[PDB]
Amino acid sequence: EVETFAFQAEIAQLMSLIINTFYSNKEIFLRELISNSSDALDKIRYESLTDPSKLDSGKELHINLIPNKQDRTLTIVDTGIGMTKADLINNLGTIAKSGTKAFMEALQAGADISMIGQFGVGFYSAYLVAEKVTVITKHNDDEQYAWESSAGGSFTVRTDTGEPMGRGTKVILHLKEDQTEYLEERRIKEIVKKHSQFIGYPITLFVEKE
Ligand SMILES: COc1c(C)cnc(Cn2cnc3c(Cl)nc(N)nc32)c1C
Ligand SMILES: [Mg+2]
C-alpha cells in the first residue's frame, strides 16, 4: 500500500541545507505554509467561477491552525484545491528544481533563508522546525493521499484511510524537541499578525483543552 520514492537530487540537497544550517529566524516556516494555503484557496475559488460544481466537495474556504501539545504536532489545514498523486510524485518536484537551484545560488552569493518563498520552494522551510512532515490531501480529480518524509533522501505516498477531507490539504508538522514554542497560542498569534495580516481567508487558531 505504501510506495517509496527518491527525491530529485536538487530537492534532497536543499532539504539537507535547511536541516543542517544554523539559522535562528525559524518562525518564517509558518508564513510560508500559510501563503501556500492562500494560493491553493485562490486556485479553487478561481476554478469555481466557471464550474461551480468544483465546490460540491465543500463551499467553505478557510485556514485552520491546530496545535497539539500531547503529540507535539502543529497542523495547518486548508480547503484549497489540493494535490493529485501526480503532483505529489512528480509535478511539484519538477517545477521546484529550477527555483531550488537559483535559491542555492542566491544563498552562497549573499541571501538568507527567509527569502526561500521568493523562489517558490517555501514548503521545505517546514524542516527548520520538523523532524517529519505528513501531508494529507484530496483533489477533486483524485483520491485522498498521505505523503510523508523525514528527509533523508526519500518520501512515501499511500492512499489515506483516515477521516475523509472533502477537499484540501493538511500539513502535519512533527516538531523537533527544542521547537515546541510553536505550540503556544501566544507565539502563533505573534507570527500570524507579524507575517500574514493581509491574507484574504479566515484563519482560525484552535485552542487546546489541555
Ligand atoms: C507534498 O508536500 C508538498 C511538497 C512536496 C511541495 N510543495 C508543497 C506546497 N504545495 C503545493 N501545492 C499545494 C497545495 Cl494545492 N496546497 C498547499 N497547502 N500546499 C501546496 C507541498 C504541500
Ligand atoms: Mg472552522
Image: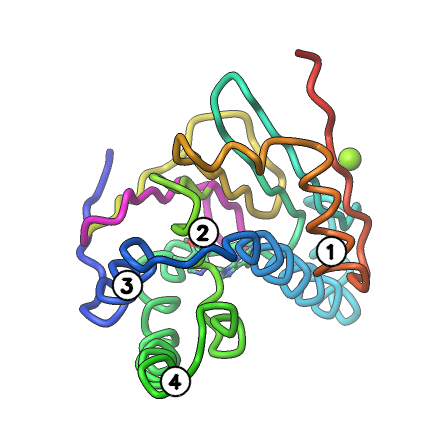
Task: Kindly identify the amino acid type of the residue bearing the numbered disc 4.
Answer: Ala
Secondary element under disc 2, as helix, strand or loop, is: helix
Q: Evaluate if marks 2 and 4 touch, with contact meaning CB atoms under 8 Å apart.
A: no
Secondary element under disc 4, as helix, strand or loop, is: helix
Which corner quadrant of the figure contains ligand 2?
top right
Task: Kindly identify the amino acid type of the residue bearing the numbered disc 3.
Answer: Leu
Between disc 2 and disc 4, whose residue precedes?
A: 4
Q: Which x, y percent locates residue 127? A: 39, 50
Q: Quadrant of the N terminus?
A: top left
Q: Evaluate if marks 2 and 1 touch, with contact meaning CB atoms under 8 Å apart.
A: no
| Left or right of 88 in this view: 141 | right
Q: Which mark is residue 90?
A: none
In the rendered view, tell whether residue 131 sits above or below residue 113.
Answer: above
Give the alpha-carbon distance from disc 2 to disc 4, as whole Å. 20 Å
The residue shown at (74%, 58%) is 194
| Left or right of 37 in this view: 90 | left
Give the alpha-carbon distance from disc 2 to disc 1, as whole Å. 33 Å
The residue shown at (64%, 55%) is 34
Can you identify the residue that label 4 sits on? 106
Give the alpha-carbon distance from disc 1 to disc 4, as whole Å. 43 Å
Can you identify the residue that label 2 sits on? 126
Give the alpha-carbon distance from disc 1 to disc 3, as whole Å. 43 Å
Question: Mark 1 Cα within 10 Å, few/some/many (few <14, many 20+)?
Answer: few
Give the alpha-carbon distance from disc 4 to disc 3, as whole Å. 13 Å
Q: Quadrant of the C terminus?
A: top right
Secondary element under disc 3, as helix, strand or loop, is: helix
Q: In terms of depth relative to the viewer, which is nearer, 9 or 179?
A: 179
Find the magenta span and give its range: 136-153
Q: Nearer the viewer, mark 1 or mark 3?
A: 3
Q: Which mark is residue 53?
A: 1
Secondary element under disc 1, as helix, strand or loop, is: helix
